[PDB]
Structure formats: structure tokens, C-alpha cells
Image (cartoon, helix red, strand yellow):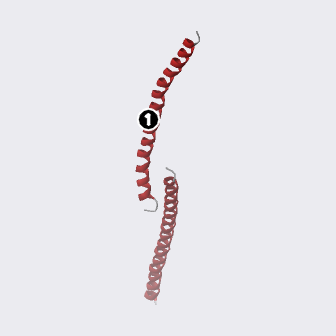
Amino acid sequence: MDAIKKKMQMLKLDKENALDRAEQAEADKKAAEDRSKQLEDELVSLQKKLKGTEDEL
Amino acid sequence: DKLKEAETRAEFAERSVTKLEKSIDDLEDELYAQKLKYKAISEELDHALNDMTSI
């Protein structure tokens, strides 16, 4: 028929929007995880440096 | 002399009626069958649309 075409297009629109949202969220989650890992790395290097300084003191 | 001509006119016109009756009836019944097939394919789509239009 015809209204089937309209409904199908509406549902394809919804799918497009949902998949776009999912992709954006996944990218941002990846970026935040990288930032957190860098922070932890620098924290541990900070502990190393502080430990060396305390040793020499 | 022209009486027989009138008889021929009547008889030759009458047979055309019989020839055309079958044609009209067959054509009308074929139209009826086509319309019935159209409705048979239409009602299934109607039910699908009943389920389809926003549930």
C-alpha cells in the first residue's frame, strides 16, 4: 500500500537517529577512558618521584 | 416484395441481440471476478495496516 511506506520511512528515521546517538556516545566513552588512564599513569609516576625524593632525604 | 426485406431486417437484428447478450454477461462477470480479486488482496493489506499504523 502507501501508508506502509510512510511508516517504514519514519522507522528508518528513528533507527538512523538512534545509531548516530550510540556512535557518538561510544566515541566519547573511549576518549574519557583514555584520559583516565593517562591520569593514573601520571599519578603512579608521581609516586615514584616522591618515593625517590623521600629516599634521598 | 419489401415485406421479406423487413423480415430479413428483423431477423438479422435479432441474432445480434443474442450474440451480444453473451458478450455483455461474460464481460460483466469477468469485471466482477477482477473486483473480487482486488478486494481479496485489499483486505489482507487492510489487516496488515490495522496492525501497522502505530500498532
**What residue is shown at x 44% (from left), y 34% (from top)?**
B30
> Which residue occupies the foreground of this view, A46 or B35?
B35
Q: Nearer the viewer, residue B16 or A26?
A: B16
Answer above or below: position of B36 versus A10.
Answer: above
Q: Would residue A7 appear left or right of B44 to someone viewing this image?
A: right
Chain ID for label 1? Answer: B
Can you name the residue that lies furthest to the bottom here?
A57
Q: Secondary structure at mark 1?
A: helix
Q: Give residue B34's position: percent from left, percent from top.
A: 45, 38
Residue at the farthest right position: B2
Q: Of the residues shown, which amino acid type is indicated by label 1?
A: Asp
Residue B13 % position (x, y): 53, 21
Question: Which residue is found at the position 49% from the left and 68% from the top?
Answer: A25
- Please tell me which residue lies in front, B47 or A26: B47
* Label 1 sits on residue: B29
Up-down relation of residue B9 to residue A26 (above or below)? above
Residue B11, percent from left and from top: 51, 18
Image position, residue B5 (x, y; %) = 57, 13
